[PDB]
Image 1 (cartoon, chains in turn purple, yellow, red):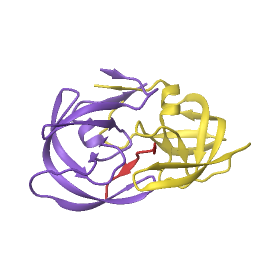
Image 2 (cartoon, chains in turn green, red, cyan):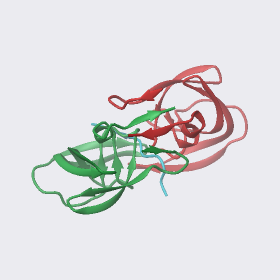
Image 3 (cartoon, helix red, strand yellow):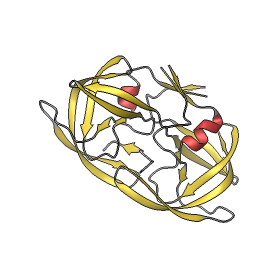
Length: 99
Length: 99
Length: 10
């Protein structure tokens, strides 16, 4: 698909059987989801954004489906204002920014 | 071009004769640059994201050259951690997301 | 609503 940027590039994702809305975000190194429960091992990390920093939990090798693409990678969970699909998973779905 | 996302999509911009580096950010509604002088009237505004809000100055109809595309639009100026090109200008250069 | 979702790794 080709996605315009006149509106926010929001898509439905599927993780752990939950449906969520997420933003395709070329300005994010990492994928960050709103607080939720994920199974298994994790490590704490500090990430930065436009307003300062937030604490997250880092979970590795998590499966997520994004616009019908199955990806498996790192997911950060914390107090982000919106679910963010960052470059770590955008590269796995083959996403490019074209102009 | 078709910019891949293996690394941060940083590009050189030119504004008021100054060369700067900025991030192509589909997760930003608006464009915000680190503190600089710009001509004309401005309005104070609060913008938010990960980590909360910052106060910026809003300037209208500012010409800016991005990857050789000469565009004109609203430019916010304030304490962003990096110069950010948001959707208001990504649309003007003709950007889409593709996968 | 907030609107700038820049995010940087540690």
